[PDB]
Image: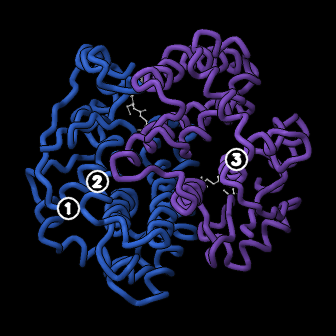
Chain colours: A blue, B purple
Amino acid sequence: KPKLHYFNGRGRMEPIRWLLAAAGVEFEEKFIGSAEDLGKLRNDGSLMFQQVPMVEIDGMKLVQTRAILNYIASKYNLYGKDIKERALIDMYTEGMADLNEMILLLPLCRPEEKDAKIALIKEKTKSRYFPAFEKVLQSHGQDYLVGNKLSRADISLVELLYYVEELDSSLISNFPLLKALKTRISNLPTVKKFLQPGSPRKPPADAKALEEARKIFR
Amino acid sequence: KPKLHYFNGRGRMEPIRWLLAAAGVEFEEKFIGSAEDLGKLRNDGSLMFQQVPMVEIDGMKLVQTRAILNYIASKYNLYGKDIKERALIDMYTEGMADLNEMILLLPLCRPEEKDAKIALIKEKTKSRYFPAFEKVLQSHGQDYLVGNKLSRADISLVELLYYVEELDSSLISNFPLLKALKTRISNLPTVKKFLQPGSPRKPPADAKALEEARKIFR
Ligand SMILES: N[C@@H](CCC(=O)N[C@@H](CS)C(=O)NCC(=O)O)C(=O)O
Ligand SMILES: N[C@@H](CCC(=O)N[C@@H](CS)C(=O)NCC(=O)O)C(=O)O
């Protein structure tokens, strides 16, 4: 069983949880709850760059989010059928990571900044990102983004759609195809289970959570 | 011939120029010199996320640095022999990307915070990154980072070694294996040509350069 090392929260590890659950893979989590917990990991020489996420899988101690995701996607055949499909998949997911990065960092923005940031995110979501993905779905009219079959791109997108919903649920409003994809994916047996209460799925970070995580990683 | 769309500067396109030259692939560049040049790319629908880097290759208009790099690495056999070798490669390159991002963003730091940033980069270079890569070279005693064969990780690392040298040439002093890799990789025919004057290799951005790019993208 793959074991995920991270604090008890979303952070950068969430995408990995989504992908494994989607692939139908059982996994364990070992939560870091103190600077000393991180310290131990860091001293065992388990973290190549002395950072987490870190995942123990197939005899490896993989570090670096993209590295972990690529390995998992390939192993479970959610990374396309050829080099060109991987290109489309990577192009789509990097765009998703860019939008997710703005949202993921919103808390660190100073109170005078935040307002300006929020407007920006919303603006880019409606004029930049959602239009781009609605357009690929439109380009071929299939239920999946690439190769007419489930891939990590579909899973990342839907994960991103839920996050956006938490910000402002009206942003997806003028994008039917994205709405249809969200429903379809949320209904796949594996994802539906992951979406239910009590799953390893993590909640949005709250004041307390943010703070406590800042102590650990200092 | 692949065509790279970016401004005449290092920016985020440089790693891609490095990889292609190393693989011995001739390419063309179409420099963006104004907001109008960029505007024409957006209006052509050539930029999926209305951003560059963008590379025209094998019939596609690839965007997103990481997407482009992964495609090129596979095409020219610089991406390992299997899923696990790709995991090591991805892990090593992502760490490299993190250090690079810090150096890349240095010119954006306000004068009052620059010194602290510079200090952080130097410290992390010596206690975090260089030790990690030296350790892997030490682990197997081979000329290359992975599979005892040239790969994108070796090419990326050396480019990074040159950037570090521009900042502080004493930073690599306690890492002989990295020093040897730098010489070894720099002597490969394709890279030696790329390092020679008059090549597509780009210079450090001077005050003016930053200023102009700042205008183009806003
Ligand atoms: N680029 C890395 C970022 C990893 C990272 O910043 N991890 C933070 C927690 S979010 C950490 O471990 N910080 C402690 C440190 O930087 O020493 C990845 O995608 O996995
Ligand atoms: N994550 C993208 C970042 C691309 C990016 O920020 N491109 C800048 C030039 S450095 C741009 O085109 N900015 C114009 C804009 O954001 O509208 C990638 O690695 O390719």
Residue A12, horizontal then vertical, whole percent:
36, 42
- The residue indicated by pointer 1 is A23
Q: Classify 10 Å Cα crowding around label 2: few (below 14), some (14-19), many (20 and above).
A: many
Along the viewing direction, whichever of A164 and B45 lies nearer the viewer: B45
* A86 sits left or right of B171 in the view: left
Marks 3 and 1, how far apart at CA = 36 Å
- Is residue B45 positioned above or below B216 on the image? below
Q: Classify 10 Å Cα crowding around label 3: few (below 14), some (14-19), many (20 and above).
A: many
| Residue located 52% across and 69% down the image | A126
User: Which amino acid does the dot numbered 3 rest on?
Assistant: Trp
* A130 sits left or right of A150 in the view: right
- The reply to whether dot 3 and dot 2 touch (C-beta < 8 Å) is no
| Residue located 32% across and 51% down the image | A71
- The reply to whether dot 2 and dot 1 touch (C-beta < 8 Å) is yes
Chain ID for label 1? Answer: A
Residue A30, horizontal then vertical, whole percent:
16, 32
Residue B204, horizontal then vertical, whole percent:
81, 35
| Residue located 77% across and 53% down the image | B218
- The residue indicated by pointer 3 is B18
Residue A25, picture quadrant: bottom left
Quadrant in which the C terminus of chain A appears? top left
| Mark 3 or 1: the one toward you | 3
- Is residue A151 positioned above or below B169 on the image? below
The reply to whether residue A119 is visible in this rendering is: no
Along the viewing direction, whichever of B12 and A159 lies nearer the viewer: B12
Dot 3: element: helix
- Is residue B163 positioned above or below A87 on the image? above
